[PDB]
Length: 137
Ligand SMILES: CCCCCCCCOCCOCCOCCOCCO
Ligand SMILES: CCCCCCCCOCCOCCOCCOCCO
Ligand SMILES: CCCCCCCCOCCOCCOCCOCCO
Ligand SMILES: CCCCCCCCOCCOCCOCCOCCO
Ligand SMILES: CCCCCCCCOCCOCCOCCOCCO
Ligand SMILES: CCCCCCCCOCCOCCOCCOCCO
Image (cartoon, rainbow, N blue to C red):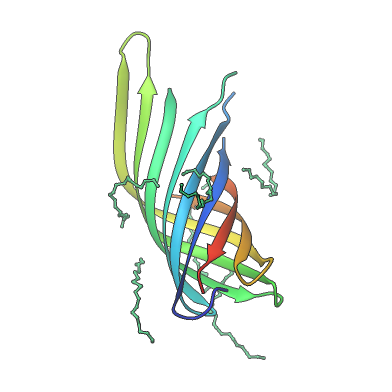
């Protein structure tokens, strides 16, 4: 994990489920100790051919543990404010907003002290994503 009392920022590519949606996101966080950090994220998803767009902003606690010196397993839990925009040909544009709990599980690999990648599955009550972050130290 990032050094205690330090910040990080990252970006991701995401995918959820015919129907496939792809998009991207950004996140920023503050690490307290090797097991606990907090993060704020923004992600969007768009429907791929053969406007359905969704966006969400979230704030979560991130709890993790080192599987190895370089690999952490982690979970995130918190809330998300979302917006989904639609485009119909009959009814024009539309959108709905909501608030929901949000969860995630993932693995993060510290490539260098400054750079880490992550692989995550996020769900609510899913979206797979790959990302990279920069640790300010
Ligand atoms: C931005 C995409 C990131 C996706 C990479 C995650 C891939 C890593 O492996 C995770 C496990 O593989 C899961 C497979 O996808 C679900 C399969 O079934 C879907 C069709 O019904
Ligand atoms: C939610 C946006 C989608 C995420 C896009 C991925 C972009 C990843 O971040 C790129 C790396 O960060 C930028 C670096 O700072 C230097 C840029 O040049 C300076 C200003 O002109
Ligand atoms: C549900 C998650 C809520 C999000 C948590 C917000 C976390 C709050 O901010 C963390 C960043 O603020 C930094 C702390 O102050 C510095 C502490 O003194 C340093 C040495 O112990
Ligand atoms: C999804 C997996 C992530 C689950 C998060 C784990 C929660 C983090 O805190 C666990 C408690 O921290 C204690 C661990 O360090 C100590 C162990 O014993 C010492 C060496 O043998
Ligand atoms: C507790 C559930 C709510 C989650 C808190 C998130 C609160 C954050 O602010 C939400 C309002 O801000 C609007 C977001 O759109 C802009 C985001 O940043 C742009 C892309 O990088
Ligand atoms: C103590 C280690 C940290 C692990 C705690 C993380 C807690 C994670 O679980 C939260 C509960 O998960 C929510 C699941 O319910 C919704 C599932 O999807 C709807 C059916 O397909």
